[PDB]
Protein backbone atom coordinates (compact mmCIF):
# COMPACT_ATOMS: atom_id res chain seq x y z
CA UNK A 1 0.00 0.00 0.00
CA UNK A 2 0.92 3.76 0.14
CA UNK A 3 2.28 3.29 3.76
CA UNK A 4 1.75 7.00 4.72
CA UNK A 5 -2.04 6.93 5.38
CA UNK A 6 -1.62 3.73 7.52
CA UNK A 7 0.54 5.75 10.06
CA UNK A 8 -1.84 8.76 10.01
CA UNK A 9 -4.81 6.33 10.55
CA UNK A 10 -3.38 5.66 14.09
CA UNK A 11 -4.15 9.35 15.05
CA UNK A 12 -7.87 8.81 14.15
CA UNK A 13 -7.93 6.32 17.09
CA UNK A 14 -7.15 9.20 19.56
CA UNK A 15 -10.93 9.22 20.45
CA UNK A 16 -11.88 12.97 20.23
CA UNK A 17 -15.48 14.30 20.72
CA UNK A 18 -15.14 18.05 19.73
CA UNK A 19 -14.08 17.70 16.04
CA UNK A 20 -17.37 15.93 15.18
CA UNK A 21 -19.26 18.81 17.00
CA UNK A 22 -17.28 21.60 15.19
CA UNK A 23 -17.88 20.10 11.70
CA UNK A 24 -21.64 20.14 12.52
CA UNK A 25 -21.39 23.84 13.65
CA UNK A 26 -19.51 24.74 10.39
CA UNK A 27 -22.33 23.04 8.37
CA UNK A 28 -25.26 24.41 10.53
CA UNK A 29 -24.29 28.09 9.94
CA UNK A 30 -25.40 27.61 6.24
CA UNK A 31 -28.80 25.83 6.91
CA UNK B 1 -6.71 13.72 23.22
CA UNK B 2 -6.09 15.96 20.17
CA UNK B 3 -9.33 18.06 20.53
CA UNK B 4 -7.96 21.67 20.10
CA UNK B 5 -6.21 21.00 16.75
CA UNK B 6 -8.66 18.27 15.60
CA UNK B 7 -11.61 20.70 15.89
CA UNK B 8 -9.65 23.45 14.04
CA UNK B 9 -8.85 21.10 11.06
CA UNK B 10 -12.54 20.02 11.48
CA UNK B 11 -13.54 23.71 10.89
CA UNK B 12 -11.70 23.65 7.50
CA UNK B 13 -13.45 20.28 6.64
CA UNK B 14 -16.93 21.58 7.72
CA UNK B 15 -16.40 24.76 5.63
CA UNK B 16 -15.09 22.95 2.50
CA UNK B 17 -17.57 20.03 2.24
CA UNK B 18 -20.72 22.30 2.14
CA UNK B 19 -19.70 23.51 -1.36
CA UNK B 20 -18.84 20.09 -2.88
CA UNK B 21 -22.04 18.71 -1.19
CA UNK B 22 -23.99 21.10 -3.50
CA UNK B 23 -23.33 18.52 -6.34
CA UNK B 24 -21.96 15.31 -4.62
CA UNK B 25 -19.74 13.47 -2.08
CA UNK B 26 -16.44 14.66 -3.74
CA UNK B 27 -13.28 15.99 -1.98
CA UNK B 28 -12.74 18.70 -4.72
CA UNK B 29 -14.15 22.16 -5.61
CA UNK B 30 -14.61 23.36 -9.23
CA UNK B 31 -13.31 26.92 -10.04
CA UNK B 32 -16.78 28.60 -9.78
CA UNK B 33 -17.73 26.49 -6.66
CA UNK B 34 -14.39 27.56 -5.08
CA UNK B 35 -15.41 31.20 -5.85
CA UNK B 36 -18.81 30.44 -4.18
CA UNK B 37 -16.89 29.25 -1.03
CA UNK B 38 -14.85 32.51 -1.05
CA UNK B 39 -17.92 34.82 -1.47
CA UNK B 40 -20.10 32.85 1.05
CA UNK B 41 -17.33 32.44 3.71
CA UNK B 42 -15.64 35.89 3.22
CA UNK B 43 -18.87 37.95 2.77
CA UNK B 44 -17.48 41.03 0.90
CA UNK B 45 -21.09 41.77 -0.32
CA UNK B 46 -21.32 44.93 -2.53
CA UNK B 47 -17.53 45.68 -2.10
CA UNK B 48 -15.08 46.20 -5.07
CA UNK B 49 -12.79 43.27 -3.94
CA UNK B 50 -14.44 40.63 -6.27
CA UNK B 51 -11.78 41.72 -8.84
CA UNK B 52 -9.22 40.59 -6.20
CA UNK B 53 -11.26 37.35 -5.62
CA UNK B 54 -11.05 36.38 -9.35
CA UNK B 55 -7.23 36.74 -8.96
CA UNK B 56 -7.32 34.79 -5.61
CA UNK B 57 -9.30 32.12 -7.57
CA UNK B 58 -6.47 32.12 -10.21
CA UNK B 59 -3.92 31.63 -7.32
CA UNK B 60 -6.08 28.68 -6.02
CA UNK B 61 -6.65 27.24 -9.58
CA UNK B 62 -2.81 27.23 -10.07
CA UNK B 63 -2.92 23.88 -8.16
CA UNK B 64 -5.42 22.51 -10.79
CA UNK B 65 -7.72 24.54 -13.13
CA UNK B 66 -10.59 22.02 -13.53
CA UNK B 67 -11.17 21.49 -9.76
CA UNK B 68 -9.01 22.23 -6.65
CA UNK B 69 -8.64 19.32 -4.18
CA UNK B 70 -9.11 19.62 -0.36
CA UNK B 71 -5.39 18.99 0.44
CA UNK B 72 -4.24 21.79 -1.96
CA UNK B 73 -7.02 24.08 -0.58
CA UNK B 74 -5.37 23.50 2.88
CA UNK B 75 -1.84 24.12 1.33
CA UNK B 76 -3.27 27.49 0.14
CA UNK B 77 -4.71 28.28 3.63
CA UNK B 78 -1.13 27.52 4.87
CA UNK B 79 0.16 30.31 2.58
CA UNK B 80 -2.76 32.59 3.70
CA UNK B 81 -1.79 32.00 7.39
CA UNK B 82 1.95 32.65 6.60
CA UNK B 83 1.18 35.89 4.61
CA UNK B 84 -0.89 37.18 7.62
CA UNK B 85 2.49 38.76 8.76
CA UNK B 86 1.61 39.44 12.47
CA UNK B 87 0.46 35.84 13.21
CA UNK B 88 4.05 34.41 13.04
CA UNK B 89 5.33 37.38 15.20
CA UNK B 90 2.68 37.50 18.05
CA UNK C 1 -17.90 31.86 7.98
CA UNK C 2 -14.91 34.31 8.04
CA UNK C 3 -14.43 34.64 11.87
CA UNK C 4 -14.91 30.83 12.48
CA UNK C 5 -12.17 30.10 9.85
CA UNK C 6 -9.87 33.00 10.96
CA UNK C 7 -9.76 31.63 14.56
CA UNK C 8 -9.22 28.02 13.29
CA UNK C 9 -6.16 29.04 11.15
CA UNK C 10 -5.13 30.95 14.36
CA UNK C 11 -5.25 27.62 16.30
CA UNK C 12 -2.63 26.09 13.93
CA UNK C 13 -0.26 29.10 14.44
CA UNK C 14 -1.10 29.25 18.21
CA UNK C 15 0.09 25.60 18.39
CA UNK C 16 3.03 25.77 15.87
CA UNK C 17 4.90 29.00 16.74
CA UNK C 18 5.42 28.07 20.46
CA UNK C 19 7.62 25.15 19.24
CA UNK C 20 9.36 26.79 16.21
CA UNK C 21 10.17 29.95 18.28
CA UNK C 22 11.24 27.93 21.41
CA UNK C 23 15.00 28.74 20.93
CA UNK C 24 14.86 31.74 18.47
CA UNK C 25 12.74 33.74 15.96
CA UNK C 26 12.56 30.53 13.80
CA UNK C 27 9.53 29.46 11.66
CA UNK C 28 10.38 25.69 11.21
CA UNK C 29 9.97 22.58 13.44
CA UNK C 30 12.89 20.17 13.97
CA UNK C 31 12.29 16.49 14.92
CA UNK C 32 12.23 17.31 18.68
CA UNK C 33 9.89 20.36 18.18
CA UNK C 34 7.18 18.39 16.33
CA UNK C 35 7.24 15.49 18.83
CA UNK C 36 7.08 17.93 21.83
CA UNK C 37 4.24 19.85 20.06
CA UNK C 38 2.14 16.67 19.65
CA UNK C 39 2.88 15.19 23.12
CA UNK C 40 2.08 18.57 24.84
CA UNK C 41 -0.74 20.10 22.68
CA UNK C 42 -2.51 16.91 21.37
CA UNK C 43 -1.14 14.31 23.90
CA UNK C 44 -1.98 10.82 22.46
CA UNK C 45 -4.59 7.98 22.32
CA UNK C 46 -2.16 5.59 24.08
CA UNK C 47 1.59 6.09 24.94
CA UNK C 48 2.25 2.73 23.12
CA UNK C 49 1.58 4.66 19.82
CA UNK C 50 4.66 6.98 20.34
CA UNK C 51 6.71 4.74 17.98
CA UNK C 52 4.10 5.62 15.26
CA UNK C 53 4.30 9.34 16.37
CA UNK C 54 8.09 9.32 15.58
CA UNK C 55 7.19 7.70 12.18
CA UNK C 56 4.57 10.50 11.61
CA UNK C 57 7.39 12.97 12.58
CA UNK C 58 9.70 11.27 9.98
CA UNK C 59 6.83 11.51 7.36
CA UNK C 60 6.51 15.27 8.25
CA UNK C 61 10.31 15.78 7.83
CA UNK C 62 10.03 13.86 4.46
CA UNK C 63 9.49 17.33 2.85
CA UNK C 64 12.97 18.75 3.80
CA UNK C 65 15.12 15.97 5.48
CA UNK C 66 16.36 18.10 8.48
CA UNK C 67 13.41 20.22 9.83
CA UNK C 68 9.82 20.80 8.48
CA UNK C 69 8.55 24.28 7.46
CA UNK C 70 5.14 25.90 8.26
CA UNK C 71 3.31 25.46 4.89
CA UNK C 72 4.51 21.79 4.62
CA UNK C 73 3.32 21.15 8.24
CA UNK C 74 -0.14 22.55 7.21
CA UNK C 75 -0.07 20.48 3.93
CA UNK C 76 0.52 17.37 6.10
CA UNK C 77 -2.40 18.45 8.39
CA UNK C 78 -4.42 18.44 5.09
CA UNK C 79 -3.45 14.74 4.67
CA UNK C 80 -4.27 14.12 8.39
CA UNK C 81 -7.67 15.83 7.79
CA UNK C 82 -8.12 13.54 4.69
CA UNK C 83 -7.69 10.47 7.04
CA UNK C 84 -11.03 11.65 8.62
CA UNK C 85 -12.53 10.74 5.19
CA UNK C 86 -16.21 10.44 6.40
CA UNK C 87 -16.31 14.24 7.09
CA UNK C 88 -15.06 14.68 3.44
CA UNK C 89 -17.80 12.30 2.10
CA UNK C 90 -20.88 13.53 4.10
CA UNK D 1 7.07 34.98 -9.95
CA UNK D 2 3.34 35.81 -9.45
CA UNK D 3 2.33 38.58 -6.96
CA UNK D 4 0.76 36.00 -4.55
CA UNK D 5 1.33 37.76 -1.17
CA UNK D 6 0.07 41.09 -2.67
CA UNK D 7 -3.40 39.47 -3.46
CA UNK D 8 -3.46 37.39 -0.24
CA UNK D 9 -2.75 40.66 1.70
CA UNK D 10 -6.25 41.81 0.53
CA UNK D 11 -7.67 38.87 2.63
CA UNK D 12 -5.37 39.43 5.69
CA UNK D 13 -6.67 43.03 5.70
CA UNK D 14 -10.32 41.76 5.38
CA UNK D 15 -10.16 39.07 8.18
CA UNK D 16 -11.88 39.72 11.55
CA UNK D 17 -8.52 39.54 13.54
CA UNK D 18 -9.48 36.46 15.68
CA UNK D 19 -6.27 34.87 14.21
CA UNK D 20 -4.05 36.98 16.52
CA UNK D 21 -6.53 36.63 19.47
CA UNK D 22 -6.52 32.77 19.29
CA UNK D 23 -2.70 32.73 18.89
CA UNK D 24 -2.29 34.82 22.10
CA UNK D 25 -4.82 32.52 23.94
CA UNK D 26 -2.94 29.34 22.81
CA UNK D 27 0.39 30.99 23.93
CA UNK D 28 -0.99 31.56 27.52
CA UNK D 29 -3.35 28.59 28.21
CA UNK D 30 -0.74 25.73 27.92
CA UNK D 31 0.82 26.62 31.38
Image: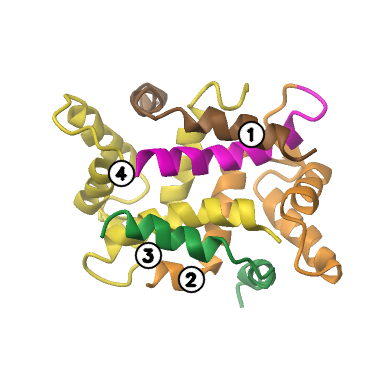
Chain colours: A green, B yellow, C orange, D brown
Determine if residue B13 is in view: yes
Magenta-colored stretch includes residue C15: yes
Contact (CB < 8 A) between labels 2 and 1?
Answer: no
Instruction: For mark 3, give the secondary structure.
Output: loop
**Residue C68 tag number:** none
Instruction: For mark 1, give the secondary structure.
Output: helix
Q: CA distance from mark 2 to mark 4?
A: 22 Å
Q: CA distance from mark 3 to mark 4?
A: 18 Å
Residue position for label 4: B41
Q: How far across and down, in percent of the image, does residue C70 sit?
A: 61, 38
Q: CA distance from mark 2 to mark 1?
A: 30 Å
Instruction: For mark 2, give the secondary structure.
Output: helix
* Mark whose residue sits in front, 3 or 1: 1
**Residue C85 tag number:** 2
Q: How far across and down, in percent of the image, does residue C64 sit?
A: 68, 43
Please report, as a chain letter, where disc 3 is located. Answer: B
Q: Is residue D22 left or right of residue C42?
A: left
Q: CA distance from mark 3 to mark 1?
A: 32 Å
Q: Is residue B12 above or below residue C48?
A: above
**Residue B27 tag number:** 3
Same subunit, tags 3 and 4: yes
Which of marks 4 and 3 precedes in the sequence?
3
Contact (CB < 8 A) between labels 2 and 4?
Answer: no
Amino acid sequence: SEGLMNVLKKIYEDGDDDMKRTINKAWVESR
Amino acid sequence: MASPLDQAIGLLIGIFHKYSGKEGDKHTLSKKELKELIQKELTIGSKLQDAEIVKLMDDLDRNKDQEVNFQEYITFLGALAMIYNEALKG
